[PDB]
Length: 258
Ligand SMILES: NS(=O)(=O)c1ccc2oc(=S)[nH]c2c1
Ligand SMILES: NS(=O)(=O)c1ccc2oc(=S)[nH]c2c1
Ligand SMILES: [Zn+2]
Image (tube, rainbow, N blue to C red):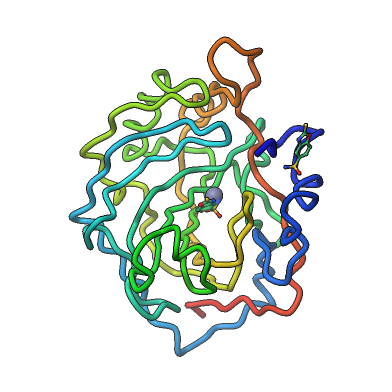
């Protein structure tokens, strides 16, 4: 894999190695709030993160992932548009070089400074690798980040970034509670989509929260000090690791609220 976010290997180039990039249910997308329809049949989302077991944080060259123990139902997402139980496996963010860009999904074309993706897989498929091969294999909870007041629950992440500056570095990250990354409201929009990075598999039920969380300028500034490169290689700041909105095609975005 040589894909990335540069001019020579960015989103415009991905289709040559991952043809599904021009598929029928690609993500992210722009959420047109006026066109999204309230669906009375949608259920309240059920986010059960009390028993979450975080293990490690890794810089994988495109973002940093906080990984969880998913060998048991410890942190799960259920309800909403989902049927079944989805286990949290990892979370990561996409962000910009400037506060005015960074999110993958947009709301009425508005771009947020960053976007958090809490990734969950459908337990009926047994493991994550099998789940990504299914249309309903994953449920990703997307949360927008706007720059304003600091998010207390995010500080432990910000403070460990110095230890995983470059690609391939990891650090112990146990006892991190992801509940501190959520906004107050769980109102959301939902639609069928895909992974936003290669392999771009069309296996995701996207659940995007309406309420952004606020993070401080200093917190996001630290995200921008990370590197896409490995140690001992020319420094390339890890910024603008977001894919732009893709064609909605034959899909409807549904709202859980009126
Ligand atoms: N993965 S990809 O985005 O299609 C892509 C784009 C440009 C590339 O140049 C080399 S060399 N490998 C590459 C892979
Ligand atoms: N950016 S994202 O769509 O949330 C996402 C989530 C899980 C993933 O697993 C692989 S592999 N690529 C992924 C992209
Ligand atoms: Zn993501």
